[PDB]
Amino acid sequence: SRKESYSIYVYKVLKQVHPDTGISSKAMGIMNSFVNDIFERIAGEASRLAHYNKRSTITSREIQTAVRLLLPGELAKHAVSEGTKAVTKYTS
Amino acid sequence: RKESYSIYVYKVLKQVHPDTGISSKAMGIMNSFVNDIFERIAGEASRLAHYNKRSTITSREIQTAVRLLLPGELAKHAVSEGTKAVTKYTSA
Amino acid sequence: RKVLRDNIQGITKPAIRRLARRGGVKRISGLIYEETRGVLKVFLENVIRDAVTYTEHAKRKTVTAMDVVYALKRQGRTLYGFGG
Amino acid sequence: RDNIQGITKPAIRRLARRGGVKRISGLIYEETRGVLKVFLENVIRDAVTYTEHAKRKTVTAMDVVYALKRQGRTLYGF
Amino acid sequence: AKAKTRSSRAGLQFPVGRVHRLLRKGNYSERVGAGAPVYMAAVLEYMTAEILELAGNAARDNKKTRIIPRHLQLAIRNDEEMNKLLGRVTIAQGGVLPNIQAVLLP
Amino acid sequence: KTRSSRAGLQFPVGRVHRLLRKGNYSERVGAGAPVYMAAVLEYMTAEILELAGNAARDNKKTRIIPRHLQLAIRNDEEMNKLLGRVTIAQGGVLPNIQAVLLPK
Amino acid sequence: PHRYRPGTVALREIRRYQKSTELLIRKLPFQRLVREICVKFTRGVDFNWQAQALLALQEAAEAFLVHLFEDAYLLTLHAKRVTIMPKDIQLARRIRGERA
Amino acid sequence: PHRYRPGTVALREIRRYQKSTELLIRKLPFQRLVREICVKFTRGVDFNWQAQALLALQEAAEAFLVHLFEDAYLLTLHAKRVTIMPKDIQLARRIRGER
DNA sequence: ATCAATATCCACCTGCAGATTCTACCAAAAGTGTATTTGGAAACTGCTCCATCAAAAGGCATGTTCAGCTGAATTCAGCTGAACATGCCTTTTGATGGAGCAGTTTCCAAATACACTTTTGGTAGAATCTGCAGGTGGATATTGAT
DNA sequence: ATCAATATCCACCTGCAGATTCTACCAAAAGTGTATTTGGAAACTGCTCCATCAAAAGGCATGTTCAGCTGAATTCAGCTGAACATGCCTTTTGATGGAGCAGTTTCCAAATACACTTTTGGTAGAATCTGCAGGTGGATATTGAT
């Protein structure tokens, strides 16, 4: 039956940054590959971080360090800024 | 309280070169090597089990992980030895 | 009138020149086409070996796109656009 | 003096000799210091990132091995 | 009491719950903390936003309203960081950057 | 009565099982998997110590040192390919001077 | 009779094919090669190929060849030549790590 | 008075240093460079370094420089030169993927 | 060739620092038995999707000829980089002081997992909508000849 | 330079294939209460590493001279590209059978969880091995002037 993807969320963000702009299905496929790739890279690094320090929990501290090791430069600064803001606004 | 593969490396060393020793730095190299080989095989087996939506890593995933990560003759020998060890273990 | 007996010869000279043009190559030696076929064959042999291994581990007999994507991944190449 | 200049001509020539280089241009040494600086910057940034995740103030050999691992280099012996 | 998504309370579009599941399901660690999927979802949303901004810009430069893989490829390789991050990534039907080296020119 | 004993191996089948369960690879670890893994680890260790000892003897030394391991790796086609991105601390390089470089 | 100088058509083709994304190898010869190579590994039992699997492999293969051409040609210019030769491709392969 | 032809000693040195495994940059300048780079990156926090961390970093940096020299020198020979030059290193780096 | 100059090879030697062996007692993993839970194979099964066969039809590949352009080969002069000597200066070695910083145990609050149903939100077709592919033409730009 | 030939650029158009919108049912996220864990705080070791201070100790910086290497210049035979002419090979909808692949059940061999007795592998000392470095001398080997 079902195959889930990030299509709906990619589309919401797309309409947020280019409202009159659409996207083809092939472009949507490479966007799903990209989102799965970033997630696997971050989660893999977070898993390794937690393992090195003999902890069994992946927390936002591990996600944030994983971002800082895997993303280049300014992308990393923005990404940790946005994640930090999300966790702050979520606690409420 | 800090474990390694030294004892086992030395056992195998004495089986294949009985008159031969090994300095502590070369033993460190050997320990890194075994952790690297283990990490590679286990990683590929983990991914194989994920791709097929199975939750168990069996010797079948190990054997496929070997056939994907080792080159040629090393894989041929390695699968022979793994098959023989597991068969001989099955016989109690 | 000459007829094909090796499939790699189906990779024709003009196809290889189109690839080389996409790579910005301006002048091509005539020895390039068989060198390129050799390189391509080796690339295909490795990737297909790995993809078929992924197939036979899944107890399947149809190579899927994900088999190929996983094979490329295991050769250090990430292919986007076929996880659908 | 400058700290990068402590990596001297003869050292860089010994490295090139291990690399089988028979003749060296006089411009090579400043290029090599540039390259070595870039390499050390990346490896040290990541190693300190790993240390500082562990709430330590001593970067270990394992931090450095992990840094090299995350840029594709596997170091044996630590 | 009525329910609001974790994405609602974090201020995001990406599915916090689904991300949390993907963290539990992927065998990364025995336990996953509460903020980890919030943080992960935010990063994914940001990355998606950045790549869609660059890809949309390429779409406009080629007088198109629809993003196609070609625009995603141009977005990647024209951006220093995006190019470094996705250096080993092939975009099916993406082509290459128009690039002729100076020597080749008449 | 060890699992290694009735597996016929020197490498510790139990410890491999523990490192597989504790390493976050999968929720369940089968029975034959750690046996097979230990068998491979032993075989791989075996071939590499065999080659490295041979190099130690070629230098008429009795003790394996990192140099002998480096020579073992880079002189063997398949090992060298498998450990291609691996650095051996104080291993040095293979003696190799290009032909164009030697006089006359 | 009008006829272009050697290299003018070459430059025009470079611009042409760098603006496009189409696959440059014909589908059928490539897939026939693929299935022939595949039959070697299987001992002669035969596997089917999803259409998407074949076009995924062709995308990857063509991207690989184009990028190898980019690197090799850098080496060509480095030898102060303009014609790609097999040694340029072999040397690029060795430096990438593929036959190092 | 005895004098070797240019290239004879250089070949002798290639053989010497390809036979050896010692670190070839002297320890203290290298470690001073690393501590300078690290203090620069921590933006004023100062970390200490296990002896083994400094020696691991030096083993890796030297293996990296040696292999960069091998590759770049392949490019040198390809240009039918014998003198390694900066453009050889720059091109080798562009082709490996390091930029 | 001849020989002189210099370097490297090879056989010794014997301590000393590093490797090996040994004794130990100990948590600590590994093994065992048992009491359950479960994941995954076997057995259909409906149903896509993959293979194949049709043979036209145009879209490309192939082969030849000829112009002109390149890679290879050769020479040579200026100058860059190698070789070699000295002397001092930065590094290496060894101990030393002690500050700070890892590493170990041990409580407990806080954070996470678990298990029970409640609500949706996301997916999958089906029904609407529309941007772009492929074809055409005119204008611009580029090229080649003189 | 002009002047002609040719190609590429760029916008038009319309119908349809692909995109977007729309509708509904259930996997799955959310809620609440509850029942394990954990990772952290606090607290005394001990390393470990940073700073220092000598003096021994080799290695780096500096200078001089010339070999021979790089970059420039020149030639030419063969090779590669451009252009054109045929003929084949890949493309292209359709059709059909069916292979093989998801989707569902049903359990049962296999894995997990818990609470037990034992065996092993790691550490700290220590005794006891040896291998190899470093130093010496003399035997071949390599290089270079002639």
Image (cartoon, coloured by chain):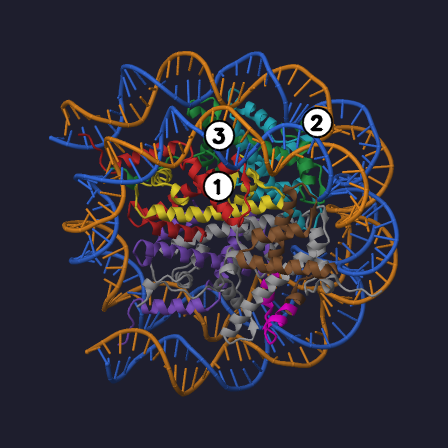
Chain colours: A brown, B cyan, D yellow, F green, G purple, H red, I orange, J blue
Specify the quadrant that holds the C terminus of chain B. Answer: top right
Q: Are marks 2 and 3 in contact (CB under 8 Å)?
A: no
Tell me the element at label 3.
helix
| Residue occupied by mark 3 | F51
Which residue lies at the image location 45% right of the left edge and 31% below the top edge?
A: F67
Mark 2, other Cα within 10 Å: few <14 / some 14–19 / many ≥20: few
| Residue occupied by mark 1 | F81
Residue G53 location, quadrant: bottom right
CA gap between label 1 and label 3 equals 15 Å
Tell me the element at label 1.
helix
Is residue B91 visible to the viewer in this orientation of the structure? no
Mark 1, other Cα within 10 Å: few <14 / some 14–19 / many ≥20: some
What is the magenta range? A12-32
Which residue lies at the image location 48% right of the left edge and 39% below the top edge?
A: F87
Q: Earlier in the sequence, mark 2 or mark 1?
A: 2
Q: Chain of mark 2?
A: F
